[PDB]
Structure formats: structure tokens, C-alpha cells
Length: 77
DNA sequence: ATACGCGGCCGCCCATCAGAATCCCGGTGCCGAGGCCGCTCAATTGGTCGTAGACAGCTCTAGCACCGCTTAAACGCACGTACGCGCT
Image (cartoon, rainbow, N blue to C red; front, side, top):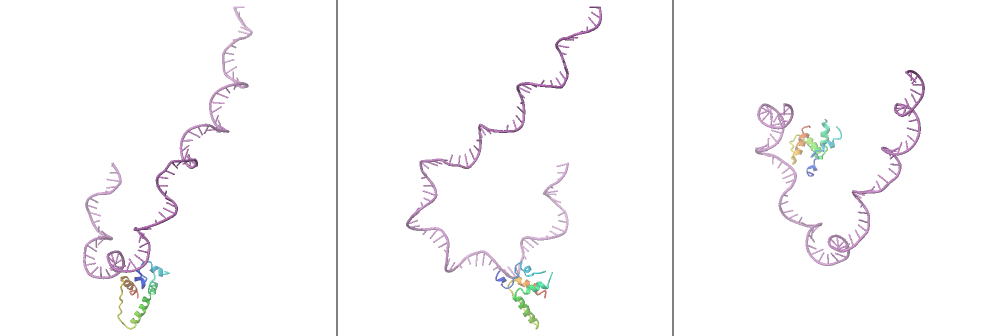
């Protein structure tokens, strides 16, 4: 569980309400979701850079829950 | 022959001496810690040897985790029958 949580913290239950130190909002949840790990900020910056030109980017992940997390992050954007 | 007197009897309030009954102080029997104790045989003391078992090294099973194709089993709801249970 530490090896799986060594890159993304959102893997348990008491983790989303701990970061949210205020009040349903939508931009604050995604803002607190991207800034929780460096791979999300750098992934969004490189994704925007690739979107400024036009390429087909793929994401290969091992954890099946992280795919759903990306399913909840990329759908809002 | 005819009229007066009275006599113990008695209800009356009023007086004296013993007996009954409550309170002020009590002895008695039962229970449970104490003490005494003493002959003594089981624990303690001082001591040796050796062996279980702690411990560190090691390797080598199996318990975990994880995933996805497949599907039997669980789910929830709709409808009515045949019991739970209440009464007499």
C-alpha cells in the first residue's frame, strides 16, 4: 500500500475531506486534486503543451483505481 | 280509745391505704477474632552439571495482491397463499 501510495495519496477513504479546508464546489476539488501530486501538475502542463500542437497522448498505469481518478479528473476539464 | 315519737336504712360527699404499671437502670448467652503451641516434615539454602532454548543466519514455502474474463449467485420487487397469532 505504501508502494501504491508513493505517487498518489487518494487511495483510501479519509483523504479528500482532509485536503479540503473549506466548503458543493467544483473548481476547488479539482484544484486540490491536481496539486496533491507533482505528476498531476506536470502531466497537465505537458498535456497542455501537447495540446498546443496536436498529438495523441496515452497514459499507461498499473493501478485500476488511478484510471478512475483520471476518469474523474479529465472529464471535468 | 287516739295522737305523738323514732329507729335503723340510706344516698351523699368526703377521708385512708394498698396494689398495679412505667421508667430507670441490667445480667446473660452466643459468636468470632485471638493466643497459644509444638512436634516436624516440607520448603529453603548453598551448590554442581548439563541441557533446553534463546538467538542469530539462512532459505525457501505460501500468503498477498492484483487483474480480467465469465456467470453463477445474490438482489430487489411483485403477488398471493397459507401460516402466525388472537379470540373464544
